[PDB]
Image (tube, rainbow, N blue to C red):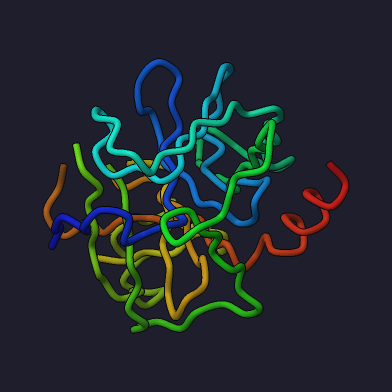
Length: 197
């Protein structure tokens, strides 16, 4: 289950702030964050280096977003293609507490353990990717090939050092696992979109 991560132990984790913390995201290079499309709104400030989001502890960088790009195929009704890119107005200064997470070159297999993080201090959960059957049986009619299940919205799911998921949806009922955007399907779109913007 959930536990307190420890300050800055997840250095690619970002907080998106519009006057309050409303979603997480993942730093993928010094200029770009990946989050969930359902997190889209105006006036986003990206907060890097955070642990307690209510206290300035000394390692934060606050940088306004300059551009938001929701996936062209995002469907808010089904949350299919629940992914968006956020550009930073100025490049983050990368250090041990503010670091990028690598994109995958291939998808992860069922049974692989992943670190899911989000928000107060940052919370963590280690959980295995569930089989396709277990995932789709939990949510009949609702899981697409762009989603996977495993044991904050917008935050990272990291497996074997790669960003494999984005926290997307899941609801409270008993044996219903979290549902995550399947990042490996979007790597080409991510790389092309950031290179063109």
